[PDB]
Length: 237
Image (cartoon, rainbow, N blue to C red; front, side):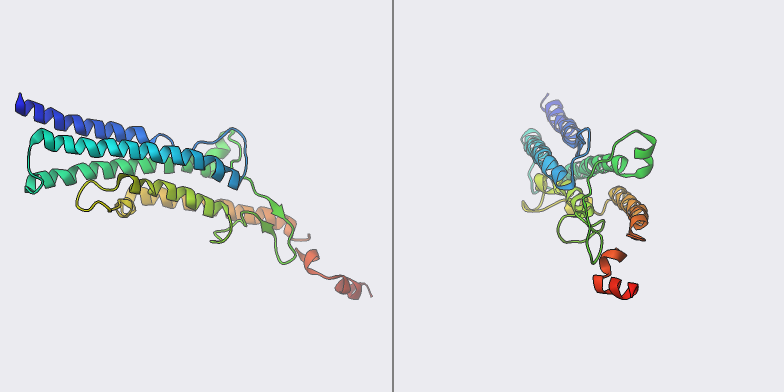
């Protein structure tokens, strides 16, 4: 019994962890029928990110409490090399689980973001772009670039991408120091790199064909806003 109990109490904790890890990943982003806007999607998804991030922490709080119930079960010292060995083994399952949970949603972006899937299906656009006429160049709210300034489709998708790495913090580590993060380990995993690198490739595809799409109008139309009235007078007579 006593042994059979300690075995199960431990096993029970691991299965519950696995179940908790599956339950929190769900679908990082959801898309609402028709298009809205870059800032409007940022506003919409902020409410869902806040709810999704908390559900991970709550699940993380349970998992952390379930680890203590394995010590109370087994009745073994934290100092002894055995329980340390396992204490690392448990965190790795949470690491791998986090890796998969982060990947699943990054793949859910990859389906919505990659042009060859959205084309084959009758799936609508998703972001909005405003276009204002500028004398010194063509002005877009998203600028159609990385920028690193104001608000851009990349800088928003950058802030989105981040929100899944931010999931590392909510767990706050299962061993050694209390203030530790997992963000380092999640970014060494090869599986996630590939998923992250696939998203960026798809972002550089659209930009080039959008640079060809915009160019069409630019050809005859940029030139006239650059030229002055006096130059127009000089050209005439």
